[PDB]
Length: 156
Image (cartoon, rainbow, N blue to C red; front, top):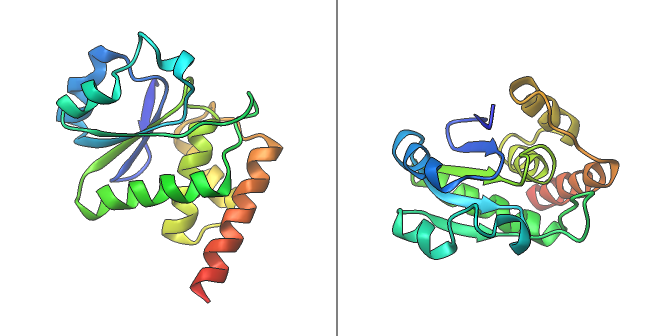
């Protein structure tokens, strides 16, 4: 409920509390973390970059302008390539935001688009089958369509 495994590499969830570190690292084999959050959101509640590293995981932090939670294309590619790095290692990646409903769902959708060449709607549908309460905003949907375009153009 707090989080869901999406595939063999990626998990999608809400803020990772410090007491969840052992479960994520040991049980879920999480060795990378993508933090779709602002500093004021993760302060106190989450591992710092250093605390993550001490626990055996590399943190990647990505921000957005407002509460509609829309990442730039650049941050999308950065995030996806990060996830792909750990996939190649046979290791897992915890992709999170505050609620694991929107900003993080968008990041996971981008990863799925890249991995399967799925459309944004197909990617979103796949996530929703597993994590019911996700919420993609129209602005988030549009950047995902742009991402799919770049992925496809690149493949040509």
